[PDB]
Amino acid sequence: GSSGSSGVRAVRKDQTSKLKYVLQDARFFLIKSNNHENVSLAKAKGVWSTLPVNEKKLNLAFRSARSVILIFSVRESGKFQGFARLSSESHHGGSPIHWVLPAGMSAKMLGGVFKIDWICRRELPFTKSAHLTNPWNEHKPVKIGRDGQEIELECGTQLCLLFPPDESIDLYQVIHKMRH
Image (tube, rainbow, N blue to C red):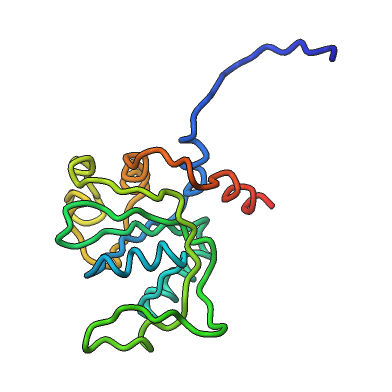
């Protein structure tokens, strides 16, 4: 072409910005489970069911805030099981999947189903997360917490970056839907 005179001010070439953007000013929610079957199933169908309180909570925080991240952490596992940003609120169409509940919990408590878009199909050892500190409690590490505990911004962010690079998921598509 022609007339391409431009004074560059800054150059970039990484896949961390988009990732940190999809959660830019978003609310992180730490969800703990009691089995791997749930995680796998959630990653297979691409959904995740939970108590009603958590559903309405995420919905309000979602419409009230930008995005809602959900870090998956397995108890007695010694590492995370990945994560996923709430691509949308819950649902109540047909019916939920045949989740794997114990001999006591009721599927009716799970309420509806949520649509999570797994951005990272990998794992993360607690060793890499063994350093962060969530001031939203008592300056304690992220390794400490229960199911359904809010997390700061820096905490969740760093925790996410820790995860390995993904080359089997469309990250841009997650940002394109937002802008449009």
